[PDB]
Image (cartoon, rainbow, N blue to C red):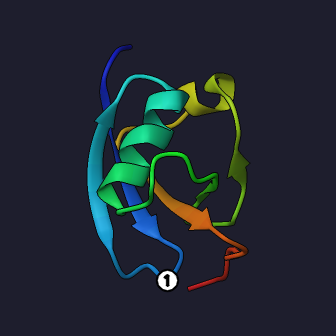
Amino acid sequence: RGKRPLKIWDSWRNVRKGVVVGTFEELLVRGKDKLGVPASEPVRVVLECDGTQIEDGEYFRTLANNTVLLLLRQGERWLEH
């Protein structure tokens, strides 16, 4: 319900940011801004724990507050640890 906190980290789990967003599309916008990714550039968002990809509002709305997500750009892939 409404705006929620989520954690958005880069592919290497190095840059680690907090965002507050209401929708998946807003997740992409703020995630890219906070990680210094140009707004046009396409990205993928995955769960930090197991690389599961999030691509829509439905799955997005199932996420708990402060779920840790990775933003993957340009061929970066999910890895363990």
Residue at x-position 43% and y-position 60%: 37
Question: Looking at the image, is 49 positioned above or below residue 8?
Answer: below
Relative placement, left or right, of 5 versus 72 is left
Numbered-mark total? 1
Relative placement, left or right, of 75 versus 64 is right
Relative placement, left or right, of 47 versus 32 is right
Q: Nearer the viewer, residue 25 or 59?
A: 25
Question: Looking at the image, is 76 positioned above or below residue 34?
Answer: below
**Quarter in which the C terminus is drawn:** bottom right
Which kind of residue does numbered mark 1 sit on?
Answer: Trp
Relative placement, left or right, of 10 versus 17 is right
User: How far across and how far down the image is residue 2, in percent?
Assistant: 34, 15
Residue at x-position 41% and y-position 50%: 31
- Crowding near the residue tagged with mark 1, few <14, some 14–19, many ≥20 C-alpha atoms within 10 Å: some
Residue at x-position 45% and y-position 56%: 38
Q: Quadrant of residue 73?
A: bottom right
Q: Quadrant of residue 47?
A: bottom right
Residue at x-position 36% and y-position 39%: 65
- Mark 1 — residue? 12
User: How far across and how far down the image is residue 68, in percent?
Assistant: 44, 57
Question: Looking at the image, is 14 positioned above or below residue 41?
Answer: below
User: How far across and how far down the image is residue 18, in percent?
Assistant: 26, 52
**Quarter in which the N terminus is drawn:** top left
Q: Secondary structure at mark 1?
A: loop
Question: Looking at the image, is 1 positioned above or below residue 51?
Answer: above
